[PDB]
Structure formats: structure tokens, C-alpha cells
Image (cartoon, rainbow, N blue to C red; front, side, top):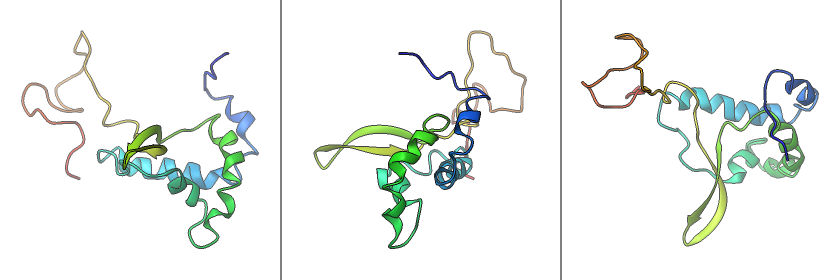
Length: 133
């Protein structure tokens, strides 16, 4: 019945909580830096891409059940992938997919408040901001 705001102090609540989540906040913040370069390096993945990611082999799921609680810590400060309900094979399930902040998200408003070179181009060379490596 109220929003979160999410500024610098909201971290003081989450600090001590980070134990198992530090691996998954590492998975999302890490894949992100390579992702803003490219379009989205992850276009669609399941809930287990991130829920298997806490551990790699046969013991993979053993902290995916803990993840149910770990999300209480994540969700007060970070969501560096997008949540969507999507239809696959005629059936609608919940999947997690990539959103990358900075470098891609650039635009011009009513007053073109920029100088010649630094950012992109204008009129000539009608592409997007990130390019082929």
C-alpha cells in the first residue's frame, strides 16, 4: 500500500542477509556488464537458470529450495534481469530474461542537449548505440 523508494539506506536492512544471495547478485550484476555491450546476451532463460546457478553439479538444487527465502533479501535491493509470463509450446509459464542498464538506453528529448561526438551520431548512420564488439 506504499512503494519502496530504494536509495542508499535500504542497504542497511539487507546487510547481514547477503550470505547465499551474494552468488545470485554476482550472476546478475556480472552477466550485465557484458550484456549492455551486446543486445541482451540472455534473451530467455527459466526460473532454475538462476535457481540452478547457486550450485553447478548434482547438488545444484540443494540451495534452490533456500532461494525461496533468499529472494526476500534480493527483492529489497536488486532485480537485474526481467520477470515475464510467456507462451511456449502453447503453454504460459514464468521465465526470467535479460535487461542491461546504461550504453543502450540513450535518447534525445525536445531540446537536443549534447555536443558533436562522445555518444553516437545524428541524421547520418541510423543504427543503435552498441555495435559488433
